[PDB]
C-alpha cells in the first residue's frame, strides 16, 4: 500500500541503503500535513449518510431514465447496491486522508476498476456525478487546508474513473 | 507492505466500517510522537557503522572459535559475510522503527532466515547473540543523544527493543 | 605472544557449507560478456551458455537449436538480450517447458531461467498472472528481459546467470530456501520430458507463510 | 500437447504396431462429426462474454458474502481476478472440446489449481460452483443455436459436460 | 506433437484469446482432407510387409558391397535390423497421415536422427533409397489426393534424412 | 495482420522450417471457406447504407434520451459521426470476410478500442445495439454458411466491445 | 506481414471505401487458382534438399575460386554459411509464393542483405548467380510433376520466377 | 572445485598448521608421476568417440529391450540422450583423472544424477552397466598404447577404475 512512509522505506530498501536525512524530511512532511487531513476525515465520517443520500439522489435527477422499469436504477435491490457502492467510495476516501497516501484508494477501488465496471455495465459517469455532488457539499462543511486535502482525494478518483 | 496507519485501516476495512473515533485517537497521538520517533531513527542511522563495529568486537571476544581456523567467521570471505549480515538485520530493524510496525522486518528480513542459517551450517545461536549485542549498543545512542530537546523516549526505546527481539527469536 | 591458533571445533571450512547445500559452484557465477570483435568460438561459448541458462539444462539437439538466431550474432545487429528474446519466443520453449507446466510453473521457471532469483513474493508472481490474459504471452516474457533488474545486471551483451544462491538485494525471505528447491543438482536439470509431468517445486501453498521443502 | 488423434497414435506406438482397423473407425467417425463439433465450439466463442457475465450474476446472488467486506471477491481487485479466472477455465474447456481430449485442459489449467486456491485462501467450493454455473449456461447456447442445420448434438454436449466436470472436480 | 489442431490451439493459447473464426477455418481444412489421408493410411498399412521386403532388397542392389562379409549389410542380424528400421519409418508415416500433421514423424524419427546415425555409422543414403523405392510402389496402389498426401510425408523424411 | 495464410507462414518462419504438409492443410481450409465468405461480403456491401440507417435509428429508439438537447445523440454533427462510425464497423467486417481472418478487425477496430471510447465517453452499449440490429437484418438476406460467417465476425466485435 | 488479400484491403482502406466489385473479382479468381498455387509450393518444399544440393554443385563448378583458399566459400565454416544462406532465400521465396506477394520475402529476407554481404566482403554477384541457378532447377520441378491432374501452371510459374528475380536483383 | 593439491592444503588448514614434511612428500611423488598421469588422460581423449561407440554396441546387444518400443532408449530422441549421457560421464571421469581427485566428478557430474534418472524412469541399473562397459574399453587403451616409453601405469589404471566405479555406484 502506497503511503509517504511506505514509499521512502521502499526506495531506501531498493537501493539497499539506510534511511538517511533525505527521507526523514519527506516523512516529516506527511506528519505535519496529517493534522489537516485528520480533521477532514472526522468531518466526512460524521456527515457520511447525508452525503450518500444526496449523491444517490442527484444521480437519478441527472439520469432520469435510470429509475424507469427495465433499467439499472430501477428496483430497490439496485438502489441499495448504488447506495452501498458510494458509501464504499467515501469510506476509502476517509481512509486515504488518514493513511496520508492514495494507497487505500488504489488497492480497493482503482485497481481492476475498468473491468468490473465493463462486465457489469456500470457507467463510470454515474459514480462521477455522485462524487461531484459530494465535492460540492464538502465545499461547505470544510475550509482551508482540510478542504484542499478532501478535494485532492475526491478528484483523484474522478480521474481514475474517467 | 504495511505500517501503523495502513494496518489500522485494514482492520477497519474487514469490519466494513468507518474508523472508530477511539481508533483515530490512537493515530492522532501517534502523530504527536512523530518528532521523537524520527530522532530515534536518526540516531541509529547516524551511528550505524559504529553500532556494528562495536557489536562485532564484543561478539568475537566472547566466541573466540568463530574467528579461529575452521570456525564459521573464518576465513576473511566468511567474516565479511557475517558482518554484512549483521548490518542488514540492523537496516531492517531501523525501517520497522520508522514504519511503527514489525511487518516490513518480518517479511523481507526474518522469514526463513533461520532455515538459511541452518542450511549453511552457520550456528543460529551466535547470530542471535550478535543481534542482541547490537540492540544494546543501538539503544545506547537512541537514548543518550546531543542537542536534542530533553524528554521521555522510553515508549520508542521499548518498541525498538521488541523489533530487535523478534529478530533474535526468529533467527534463534 | 602466545600465537595459539588451533584447529577449532566445527572445522567447517570454506567449501563444506556449499557442498552441504550441494550448489557445487552453481551459486558462484562468472558472467560472460560479448565483444564487438569476438572469435566465433567466443560466440559459440555464449550460445552454449545462453541455452543452458534459459533452458532447463535440458538436452538440446542440433535440430532444436534455431540457426537464424545463431546467425546474426556473428553479424551483429542483434543485442544478446535480444538474442535471448528470440529464444523463448521460440516455439521450442513454448511447446516444451511452457505447455505441460501450469501458468505458475513457467513463471517461476522463467524467473529462474532468465534471472537467478526465485520469486520473493506471491504478489509479483500474481502480476505476471494478470498479464497472461491481459496481454499476449510474448509480451510477458518480453517484460522480464525488459524489466529493470534484468537490465541492471547482465543488462546488455551478457548471458543471464543464476545469481540466486548468493546475497542479492531486496530478497524478501526464503531466497535460499526457494532457490534450494528450484535448483536440483548441477548434473540434474529440469526436464521437458519427465514422469509425473512437471509440477512447481515451490509449494503453491507457500510463497507467503513458510519456507519450502523439496527433494534434492 | 495432445488430442484425440495423436493420443491413439501414441498408444499404438507402445504396442509397437500399426493402427488397428477398429481404432481407425473411432477416428473415421470422429471426422464425420467434425462439422457438429466445430459449431459447438463456435457457439461458445460467440457467446463467451455473456456466458461469464451470466454465471457471475448468479454466483453472487447465491453467495452474497463473497462480495461483502471480508469475503474473497471483495474488493474490486479481487473481484477482477475472480472474473478473469472463470474466463480462463472456459477458454481451456473450449480448447479441449475442439481437440477431442481433456489433456490440454488438465495440463495447462487444472494441474496445481486446487493448491493455488488453497494457498490464497480462495474457497475451492465456490470456484467449483461457478464452473458448473458456467457449464449450464454454455450448454444452453451449444444446444439451441440459430441458422444451423437441425440435428442431434447430444454426443458432443455430454463430452462438453465431462470437461466442465473434470474442472469442477480437480478444483474442488 | 505438431498437428493442425494442436497448432491453432497453441497459437490461440499464446495470444491468450478464444478460438475465433480464423483458426476454425484452418481446423476445417484438416478435417476435410482427412478422408483422403485416412484412405492412404489404409493402403500403406495393408501392403506394409511387401513394401518393406522390396525396399530392403533394393538397397542391396543399389549398394552391392554391403552384403559382402565384414560389411554392415552382412549377416542376418543386420538384415533383420535393416528391416525393422524401415518398418518403423513406414509405421510412423501412417501415423502422420492419420494425425494430420508431421508431428509423429518429427518426434520419433527426426529429432536426434543425425547423431544416432553418426554414432552407429548408418549412412542416410541407404534409408533414402528404401523410401524412394517405396514411393515408386505407392505410386501404383494410390491415386489423386490420397497419393499426393502419401508422397508429402514420405518426402518430408527424405528431406530430413538428407 | 492475422489471416490463416499469414499465420502459417509466420509460424513456419519462426521455426526456420519449410512449409510442410501441416500448414498447407490449414491453408486449404481457408480459400475453401472463402467462397461462402465472399458471397456474404457482396451481400453486406450492397445493402450497406440501408443497414446503417436502420442501425443508427434503432439506437435512438433504444436510448430515447440521446436525442434530447445537451446529450450526445443530439445535433446533426453527432448524428453524422454516429453514422460514419457504424459504416466503419461494417466496412471492416466486410474486409475481414474477404481476408479470411479477424486481422483487419483487430488492428483497426479492436486494439485501443477501450481508451478511445473512455476518453470520448462513447458507451460501448450503443455500438452493440447497432450491431445486433444489423445481425437481425443480415439474418434475412443471407442463409447457410454465408450467414454463419457473417455472424461470427459481427459477434467477434460484440465480444470485443463488451 | 502481408499477402495478396490483406494488400487489396489496405489499399481500399485508405480510399475509405468498401471493396470495388472489380477488385473482388481479382480475389475471387485468385481463390480458384489456389489448388494450383498450393501444388506449386508443395513441389518446391518436397524437392527442397535437392534444389539446393544441385544449385551448389553448379555454382562451385563455375566459380572455382570461391572454394579455393582466400575465396569466400573457404574454409568449411564459411562454406556452411553459404549453403545455409541459399536455403534461407529459397525458404522465403516459397513463403511468398503461397502468400501471393513479394513482401514477406523482401522484408524479412532481402532488405539490407546486399549491404551485409558488402560489409563481409562476400561477392554479391556470385550470390545472385546462385539464386538463379536455384530458380531454374526449382521451376524444373514445379513444372514437370507426376500424379497431379494435368493443366496449365504458367501463370504461377512466372510469378515464381519474379520472386526469384526480386531476390537476385536486390542482392546484386 | 578441488584437486589433489588443493585438497591436501584444505585439510592442513583446518588443523591450522603448515604442511607436514611427510605430506609434501605425497605431493612431491605425485608430481613425478605426472608424465604417466598425463599420457593416461591423453589415451582416453584420443580414443573417446570409439570407447563410447563400442560400449553402446555391447550395451544394446545385451539389453535388447532398451531399443524396443516401450523401452527407455527408444525412440531416436531418447537414444540420443543415452549416448550423450555416456559421453558426459566419461568426460568428467577424464577430468577427475587429471585432477587426481574424485570431487570434480562427484559434484558436477554425479550430483543429483540418480534422482534425475529416477524422475525420467530410466533404469539406473542399465546406466551403471554402461558405465562399466565403458570402463573396461577405456582401460584397454590406457594400458596398451603405442610409441609411449614402456613402464608401469597400474597405479593410475586402478585410480581410473575407482572413478568409473564411484560413477557406477552413485548412479545405481
Ligand atoms: C449507482 C451509481 C448505480 C448502481 C450500481 C450497481 N452496482 C452493481 C454491481 C456492482 N457494483 C460494484 C461496485 C463495487 N462493489 C465493490 O465491492 C466495490 C469496491 C469496494 C465497488 C465500487 C460491483 C463490484 C458490482 C458487481 C457485483 C455486485 O453484485 O456488487 C449493480 C448490480 C448490477 C448487476 O448486474 O449485478 C448495480 C445496479 N445501482 C443503481 O441503481 C445505479 C445506476
Ligand atoms: C554472523 C552474525 C554469523 C554468521 C553468518 C553468516 N552468514 C553467511 C552467509 C549468508 N548469510 C545469508 C543470509 C541472508 N540472506 C538474506 O536474505 C538475509 C537478509 C534477510 C541475510 C542476512 C546468505 C544469503 C548467505 C550466503 C551467501 C553469502 O555468503 O553471501 C555466512 C558465510 C558462510 C557461507 O559459507 O556462506 C556467515 C558466516 N556466521 C558467523 O560467523 C556469525 C556467528
Ligand atoms: C528521543 C530518543 C530523544 C529525544 C527526542 C525529542 N525530539 C523532540 C523534538 C523534535 N525533534 C525533532 C527532529 C526532527 N523533526 C523532523 O521533522 C526531523 C526530520 C528532518 C527531525 C530529525 C524536531 C523538529 C523536534 C521539534 C523541536 C525539538 O527539537 O524539540 C522532542 C520534544 C518532544 C516532542 O517532540 O514531542 C524530544 C523529546 N529527546 C530525548 O529525550 C532523546 C534525546
Ligand atoms: C544411457 C546410457 C542410458 C540413458 C540415458 C538417458 N538420459 C535421459 C535424460 C536425461 N539425462 C540427463 C542427465 C544429465 N544432465 C546433465 O547435465 C548431465 C551431465 C552433467 C547428465 C548426464 C538429464 C537431465 C535428462 C533429462 C533431459 C530432458 O528432460 O530432456 C534419457 C531420456 C529420458 C527423458 O524422458 O528425457 C535417457 C534415455 N537411459 C537409458 O535408457 C540408457 C540405459
Ligand atoms: C472466482 C470464480 C473465485 C475466486 C478467484 C480468485 N483467484 C485468485 C487468485 C489466483 N487464482 C489463480 C489462478 C490460476 N493459477 C494458474 O496457474 C491458473 C491456470 C493456468 C489459474 C487460472 C492464481 C495463480 C492466483 C494467484 C494470483 C492472483 O492473485 O491472481 C484470487 C485472489 C486471491 C487473493 O486473496 O488476492 C481470487 C479472488 N475467488 C472467489 O472469490 C471466487 C470463488
Ligand atoms: C450442434 C451443437 C448443433 C448443430 C450443429 C450442426 N452443424 C451441422 C453442419 C455444419 N455446420 C457447419 C459449420 C462449420 N463448418 C466449418 O468448417 C466451420 C468453420 C469454418 C463452421 C462454422 C458446416 C459447414 C456444416 C455442414 C453444412 C451444414 O450446415 O449443413 C449439423 C448437421 C450435421 C452434419 O453436418 O454432419 C449440425 C447438427 N445443429 C443442431 O441442431 C445443434 C443444436
Ligand atoms: C538398413 C538400411 C541397414 C541396416 C540397419 C542397421 N541398423 C542398425 C542399428 C540401429 N538402427 C536403428 C534405428 C532405429 N531405432 C529406433 O528406435 C528408430 C526410430 C524409431 C530407428 C530408425 C537404431 C536406433 C540402431 C542403433 C542401435 C541398435 O543396435 O539397433 C544396425 C546395427 C549397427 C551396429 O553396429 O550395431 C544396422 C546394421 N543393416 C543393413 O544391413 C543396412 C546397411
Ligand atoms: C453512435 C452510436 C453515437 C455517436 C458516435 C460518436 N462518435 C464520436 C467520436 C468518435 N467516434 C470515433 C470512432 C471511431 N473513429 C475511428 O477512427 C474508429 C476506428 C476505425 C472508430 C470506431 C472516434 C475516433 C471519435 C473521436 C472524435 C471523432 O469524431 O473522430 C462522437 C463525438 C464525441 C465528441 O464529443 O467528440 C459521437 C457523438 N453519435 C451519436 O449521436 C451516438 C450517441
Ligand atoms: C552463398 C550463396 C554465398 C555466400 C554467403 C555467405 N554468407 C555468409 C554470412 C552470412 N550470410 C547471411 C545471410 C543471412 N542471414 C540471415 O539471417 C538472413 C535472412 C534473415 C540472411 C539472408 C548472414 C546474415 C551472414 C552473416 C554471418 C554468418 O556467419 O552467416 C558467409 C560467411 C561470412 C563470413 O565471413 O563468416 C558467406 C560465405 N558467400 C559465398 O561465398 C557465396 C557466394
Ligand atoms: C501446377 C504447378 C502443376 C499442377 C497443379 C495442379 N493442381 C490441380 C488441382 C489440385 N491440386 C490439389 C492439391 C492440393 N490441394 C490442397 O489443398 C493441398 C494441400 C493440402 C494440395 C497439395 C488439389 C486438391 C487439386 C484439385 C483436384 C485434384 O485432384 O488435383 C490442377 C488442376 C486444376 C485445378 O485447379 O483443379 C493442376 C494443374 N499440375 C500440373 O499440370 C502442373 C505441372
Ligand atoms: C601409462 C598409462 C603408459 C605409459 C606412460 C608413460 N609415459 C612416460 C613418460 C612421458 N609421458 C609424457 C607425456 C606427456 N607429458 C606432457 O607434458 C604431455 C602433454 C603435452 C604428455 C602427453 C612425457 C613428456 C614423458 C617423458 C618422456 C617419455 O615419453 O618417456 C613414461 C615413462 C616414465 C615416466 O615417469 O615418465 C611412461 C611409462 N607407458 C606405458 O607403457 C603405459 C601403458
Image (cartoon, coloured by chain):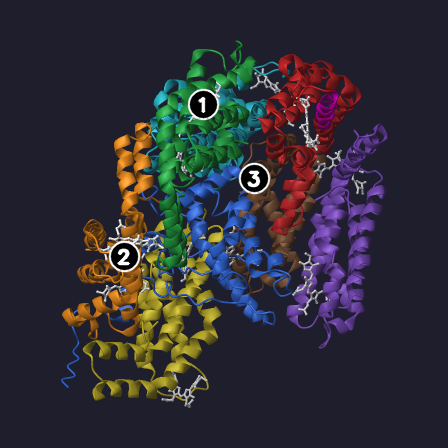
Chain colours: A green, B orange, C blue, D cyan, E brown, F red, G purple, H yellow
Residue D160 is situated, as x and y percent measured from the top left of the image, at: 48, 24
Residue B116 image label: 2
Q: Alpha-carbon neighbours of circle 3 within 10 Å: few (<14), some, or many (≥20)?
A: some
Tag 3 subunit: E
Give G53 or C137, whichever is nearer the viewer: C137
Q: Residue at x 78, y 49 (%)?
A: G141
Residue at position x 60%, y 57% in the image: C69
Question: Which mark is in front, 3 or 1?
Answer: 1
Which element carries disc 3, helix, strand or loop? helix
Tell me if A71 is positioned left or right of E161 in this view: left
**Vertical side of H66 occupied by D13: above or below:** above
What's the distance in space between the residues labelled 1 and 2, CA to CA?
44 Å
Residue located 74% across and 15% down the image: F141
Q: Are marks 3 and 1 on the same chain?
A: no
Instruction: Indicate left or right for C83 with G18 as reference.
Output: left
If the image is split into quadrants, where does the N terminus of chain C sit? bottom left
Residue at mark 3: E15
Which quadrant: the C terminus of chain C?
bottom left
Q: Specify the quadrant of the image occupied by residue B145.
A: bottom left
Q: Which residue is mark 1?
A: D56
Using the rendered image of the protein, determine whether residue G144 is visible from the camera's viewpoint.
Answer: no
Q: Secondary structure at mark 1?
A: helix
Disc 1 crowd rating (10 Å Cα; few below 14, some 14-19, many 20+) is many
The reply to whether the residue tagged 1 has its Cβ within 8 angstroms of ligand 1 is yes
Marks 3 and 1, Cα distance to the nearest angstrom?
24 Å
- At which x and y percent is residue H152? 33, 85
Q: Position of residue C131 (x, y in %)?
A: 50, 41
Magenta part of the chain: F76-88
Distance from disc 3 to disc 2, alpha carbons, whole Å, reads 40 Å
Circle 1 chain: D
Q: Nearer the viewer, residue E44 or F101?
A: F101
Which residue is at the front of the view, G49 or D158? D158
Amino acid at each position: 500500500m502506497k503511503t509517504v512512509i511506505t514509499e521512502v522505506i521502499a526506495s531506501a530498501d531498493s537501493q539497499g541503503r539506510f534511511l538517511n536525512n533525505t527521507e526523514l524530511q519527506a516523512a516529516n512532511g506527511r506528519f505535519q500535513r496529517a493534522t489537516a487531513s485528520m480533521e477532514a476525515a472526522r468531518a466526512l465520517t460524521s456527515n457520511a449518510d447525508s452525503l450518500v443520500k444526496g449523491a444517490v439522489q442527484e444521480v437519478y435527477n441527472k439520469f432520469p431514465y435510470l429509475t424507469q422499469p427495465g433499467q439499472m436504477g430501477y428496483g430497490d435491490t439496485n438502489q441499495a447496491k448504488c447506495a452501498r457502492d458510494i458509501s464504499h467510495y467515501l469510506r476509502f476516501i476517509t481512509y486515504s486522508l488518514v493513511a496520508g497516501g492514495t494507497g487505500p484508494l488504489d488497492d480497493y477501488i482503482v485497481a481492476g476498476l475498468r473491468e468490473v465496471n465493463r462486465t457489469f455495465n456500470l457507467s463510470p459517469s454515474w459514480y462521477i456525478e455522485a462524487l461531484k455532488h459530494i465535492k460540492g457539499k464538502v465545499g461547505s462543511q470544510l475550509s482551508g487546508q482540510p478542504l484542499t486535502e478532501a478535494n485532492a482525494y475526491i478528484d483523484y478518483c474522478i480521474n481514475a474513473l474517467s | 507492505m504495511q505500517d501503523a496507519f495502513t494496518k489500522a485501516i485494514v482492520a477497519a476495512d474487514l469490519r466494513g466500517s468507518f474508523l472508530s473515533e477511539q481508533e483515530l485517537n490512537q493515530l492522532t497521538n501517534l502523530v504527536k510522537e512523530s518528532n521523537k520517533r524520527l530522532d530515534a531513527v536518526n540516531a541509529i542511522t547516524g551511528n550505524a557503522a559504529e553500532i556494528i563495529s562495536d557489536a562485532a568486537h564484543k561478539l568475537f571476544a566472547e566466541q573466540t572459535d568463530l574467528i579461529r581456523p575452521g570456525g564459521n567467521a573464518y576465513p576473511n570471505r566468511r567474516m565479511a559475510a557475517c558482518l554484512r549480515d549483521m548490518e542488514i538485520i540492523l537496516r531492517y530493524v531501523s525501517y520497522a522503527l520508522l514504519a511503527g510496525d514489525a511487518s516490513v522486518l518480518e517479511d523481507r528480513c526474518l522469514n526463513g532466515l533461520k532455515e538459511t542459517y541452518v542450511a549453511l551450517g552457520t550456528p543460529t545461536r551466535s547470530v542471535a547473540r550478535a543481534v542482541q549485542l547490537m540492540k544494546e549498543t543501538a539503544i545506547g545512542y537512541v537514548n543518550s543523544p546531543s542537542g536534542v530537546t530533553r524528554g521521555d523516549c522510553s515508549a520508542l526505546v521499548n518498541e525498538a527493543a521488541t523489533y530487535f527481539d523478534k529478530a533474535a527469536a526468529s533467527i534463534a | 605472544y602466545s600465537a595459539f591458533v588451533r584447529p577449532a571445533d566445527q572445522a567447517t571450512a570454506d567449501g563444506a557449507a556449499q557442498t552441504k547445500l550441494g550448489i557445487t559452484a552453481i551459486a558462484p557465477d562468472q558472467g560472460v560478456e560479448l565483444r564487438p570483435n569476438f572469435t566465433e568460438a567466443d560466440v559459440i561459448t555464449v550460445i552454449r551458455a545462453a541455452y543452458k541458462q534459459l533452458f532447463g539444462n535440458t538436452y538440446i539437439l542440433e535440430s532444436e537449436r534455431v540457426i537464424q538466431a545463431e546467425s546474426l550474432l556473428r553479424n551483429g545487429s542483434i543485442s544478446v538480450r535480444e538474442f535471448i528474446r528470440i529464444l523463448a519466443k521460440s516455439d521450442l520453449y513454448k511447446e516444451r517447458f511452457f505447455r505441460c507446466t501450469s501458468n505458475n510453473r513457467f513463471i517461476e521457471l522463467n524467473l529462474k531461467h532468465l534471472l537467478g532469483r526465485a520469486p520473493y513474493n506471491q504478489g509479483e508472481i500474481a502480476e505476471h498472472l494478470d498479464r497472461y490474459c491481459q496481454s499476449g504471452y510474448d509480451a510477458e516474457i518480453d517484460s522480464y528481459i525488459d524489466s529493470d533488474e534484468y537490465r541492471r545486471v547482465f543488462g546488455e551483451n551478457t548471458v543471464p546467470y543464476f545469481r540466486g544462491f548468493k546475497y542479492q538485494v531486496g530478497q524478501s525471505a526464503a531466497a535460499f530456501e526457494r532457490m534450494r528447491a528450484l535448483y536440483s543438482g548441477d548434473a540434474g536439470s529440469d526436464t521437458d520430458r519427465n514422469q509425473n509431468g512437471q509440477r512447481t517445486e515451490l509449494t503453491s501453498g507457500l510463497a507467503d507463510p513458510a519456507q519450502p521443502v523439496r527433494a534434492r
